[PDB]
Image: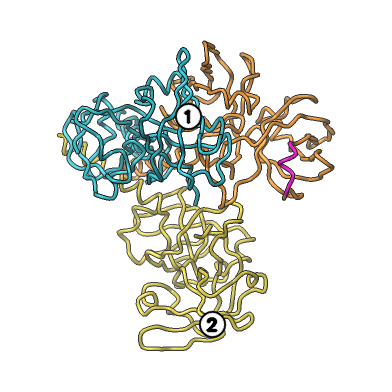
Chain colours: A orange, B cyan, C yellow
Amino acid sequence: MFTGIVQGTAKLVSIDEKPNFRTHVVELPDHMLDGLETGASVAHNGCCLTVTEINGNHVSFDLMKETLRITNLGDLKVGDWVNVERAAKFSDEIGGHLMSGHIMTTAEVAKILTSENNRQIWFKVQDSQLMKYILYKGFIGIDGISLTVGEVTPTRFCVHLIPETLERTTLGKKKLGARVNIEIDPQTQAVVDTVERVLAARENAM
Amino acid sequence: MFTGIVQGTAKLVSIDEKPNFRTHVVELPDHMLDGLETGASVAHNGCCLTVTEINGNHVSFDLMKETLRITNLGDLKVGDWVNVERAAKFHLMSGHIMTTAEVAIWFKVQDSQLMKYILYKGFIGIDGISLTVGEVTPTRFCVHLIPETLERTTLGKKKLGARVNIEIDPQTQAVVDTVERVLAA
Amino acid sequence: MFTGIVQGTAKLVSIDEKPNFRTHVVELPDHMLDGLETGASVAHNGCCLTVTEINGNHVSFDLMKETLRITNLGDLKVGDWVNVERAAKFSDEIGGHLMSGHIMTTAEVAKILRQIWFKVQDSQLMKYILYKGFIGIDGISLTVGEVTPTRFCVHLIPETLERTTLGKKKLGARVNIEIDPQTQAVVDTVERVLAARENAM
């Protein structure tokens, strides 16, 4: 599990390609190393990966072709940067929302409205069926970033940013068109799914 | 995430106003400073804000356009007090303000349409305080407050016509929306 | 708190009966002993219990008379096995599906094909048991398979089957049930809302 509070941005240092997967080597922030052992789970742009090897501030991970296909991770190139977050423990506060690290969909940066001191981004969902999990003032995961859902529509939703966000993540550098990993708030999906089942159940019981 | 159990009140000691943006400096109780770091979340009157700077017990937070638009924080004046809560650990609150209400305790809901989420025997977030809804009407609702609560928050000091931040219970919102979308059909 | 991720199985090596309570001594997997102290919470078959004593790898707990009729723990005989899990630790990575170790009812295995069908003791609770939802069985975090107004099933993977005592259960066996807390609230909110909807009429 993750909080959506990015602990750092790591740069992609090398890619080792294989038939069924790809190896990603990142240079991770020094503070992220203590306690870091192989097999640990780190989120890359919100996608949960496991440590395979560590060398100084250089950490390794393997990506199955599914992951590459389904997330923006498969489009990364060396020198590119990702948001990183180590797994959450019971002693950590949840600065954001409780995130799985499970990416199924991506969204596209549809529009950016920049003004003095402010930045609002609009995203367009790939799966409109998913908008039902994206509520006004709700939570949403973006490239591993926990964010408040601004105005939403049937096909898009937007978010308002603070400087802090722009200074800690890669979000601010994403251009129009950019594909971002999306993660629906698990707790929200659960609520919604549960209601539908109840309503279905009741409909039949009639 | 927050619990809605206020951990303290803090005094606003500095305000930096820029177009569509403020930076508030609050003086935090020493017991809330423990383990606080920049980037962390703290809710001010139920509103999630992010620490930008720590100077002793003086803690900075930026307030952006939407925040200013939707909450009563922009109304704060130096020397004013806010309900503060550090982020939860292991009612469960998002820290996302939907609207504000006026003390009419009975509250007159500014955006009356949101009443569909304010229900009897239900939870609600008032200025960061988790509460259960008492009686309602189409335009307003009531909450029953207790002594410790009044003393430990700025809610006590809240006078007729004063505005409060309303956090809709995320669960209820999800349910309500869901129900309608379904039963619309 | 608990995750629904069973940490092991332990054999009941002793039962000391009293009028008001009972004492079960289990033999805990060695891996579960480091850090364990009296007062520690350990779930047995998904039911939260407290360590009264530690004699080597044999750990003691007392069980209230009520808890005994209410759960399957009362059914235990020396030599029987239980699912065990220590409550979570600060340092534990957040995982599983947070369960409180509180058993609302039990169910009987009614058919086995691994797909197990169950029969709930307190059937008013079926409204919290939903297809595709979560359910706690003898402290195991599972997913509800098909459901009837009477019974529900689960489909078991071979690991689980050999990490827990679930796979060893036979027809007519009683299992401890933990209703997903968040599901209750939701199920509850729903009905509230629907009510409002009619009352507002």
Numbered label attached to residue C25: 2
Q: Is residue B107 above or below residue C38?
A: above
For discs 1 and 2, the disc positioned in front in the rendered view = 1
Residue drawn at (34%, 53%) of the image: C127
Position of A9 with respect to B125 (left or right) is right
Q: CA distance from mark 1 to mark 2?
A: 57 Å
Q: Which residue is mark 1?
A: B25
Residue C89: % across, % down:
57, 60
How many residues crowd around disc 1 within 10 Å: few (fewer than 14), some, or many (20 or more)? many
Dot 2: element? strand
Residue A202: % across, % down:
31, 44
Q: Is residue A136 visible?
A: yes
Numbered label attached to residue A83: none
- Which range is magenta? A29-34
The answer to which quarter of the image holds residue B26 is top left
Q: Give yes or no for residue A32 being in the magenta stretch.
A: yes
Q: Give yes or no for residue C120 being in the magenta stretch.
A: no
How many residues crowd around disc 2 within 10 Å: few (fewer than 14), some, or many (20 or more)? many
Residue A134: % across, % down:
46, 29
Q: What chain does badge 2 belong to?
A: C
